[PDB]
Image (cartoon, coloured by chain):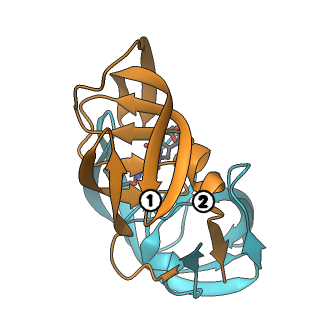
Chain colours: A orange, B cyan
Amino acid sequence: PQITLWKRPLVTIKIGGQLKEALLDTGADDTVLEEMNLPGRWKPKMIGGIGGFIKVRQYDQILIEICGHKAIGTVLVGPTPVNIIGRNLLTQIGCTLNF
Amino acid sequence: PQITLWKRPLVTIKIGGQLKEALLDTGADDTVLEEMNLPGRWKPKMIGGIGGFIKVRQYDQILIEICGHKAIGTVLVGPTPVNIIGRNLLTQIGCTLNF
Ligand SMILES: COC(=O)NC1(C(=O)N[C@@H](Cc2ccccc2)C[C@H](O)[C@H](Cc2ccccc2)NC(=O)O[C@H]2CO[C@H]3OCC[C@H]32)CCCC1
């Protein structure tokens, strides 16, 4: 589909057997989701935003379905105010900016 | 144009007569540029993102050209790590997400 930017581009995602709302974020290198208890191994990581850095848990080869489009990649989990779908997954669903 | 997301969606912008590189950021409500001198009155403001808040100078009704498209809107200037073009200006140039 096509998504205008009058409002935040929020969509439904499916991850780890749960439905959530997440922000399609072309300004994000990585995908960062709100605290959730995903199974399997993880590694500590630090990611920076405009205000500084936060600690997150890095999970690899995680499946996320974004508006019916599936993507598999690295997902970071930590105290973020919003679920962020970043370019590592947006590329996999064929997402482009157009003007 | 149509822009894919394998690399950061950086474009050249012209503001205050000066050229800069900026990130087309669908995950940003607002446009925030690195420290620079701009003509016109400004008001102090604060914006929050991942990591916390930064103090910015808010310029209203600023002319800015983004990849050959003109916009006139609010520009925040402060210690942001990267120049980000947010939805307030992305809407003006007709930018949409598509997949
Ligand atoms: C490689 O570094 C990243 O990519 N790290 C992330 C990031 O924070 N990237 C930011 C750019 C950027 C690039 C390098 C270093 C610092 C910053 C841009 C993101 O879209 C961010 C997402 C977001 C949305 C709502 C609330 C909070 C965070 N939006 C944002 O901060 O927007 C601002 C301006 O407008 C306002 O509305 C939203 C908030 C305000 C993306 C993944 C994790 C962090």
Q: Which residue is mark 2?
A: A93
Label 2 element class: helix
The residue drawn where x is 43% and y is 19% is A46
Q: Residues within 10 Å of mark 2 (few under 14, many from 20)?
A: some
Give the amino acid type for the residue marked by disc 2 in the picture. Answer: Ile
In the rendered view, would you say A45 is above or below A6? above
The answer to whether B33 appears left or right of A9 in the picture is right
Q: Would residue B85 be visible to someone looking at this image?
A: yes
Residue at the limit of the structure toward the front, as seen here? A17
CB atoms of marks 2 and 1 within 8 Å: yes
Q: Residues within 10 Å of mark 1 (few under 14, many from 20)?
A: many
For mark 1, name the chain. A
Q: Which residue is mark 1?
A: A66
The span from disc 2 to disc 1 (Cα, nearest Å) is 8 Å
**Is the CB atom of the residue marked by disc 1 within 8 angstroms of ligand 1's nearest atom?**
no
**Could you say where residue A1 lies in the image, as x and y percent from the top left?**
52, 81
**Could you say where residue A65 lies in the image, as x and y percent from the top left?**
44, 54
Point out the image quarter for the C terminus of chain A: bottom right
Q: Would residue B35 be visible to someone looking at this image?
A: no
**Could you say where residue A74 lies in the image, as x and y percent from the top left?**
52, 31
Give the amino acid type for the residue marked by disc 1 in the picture. Answer: Ile
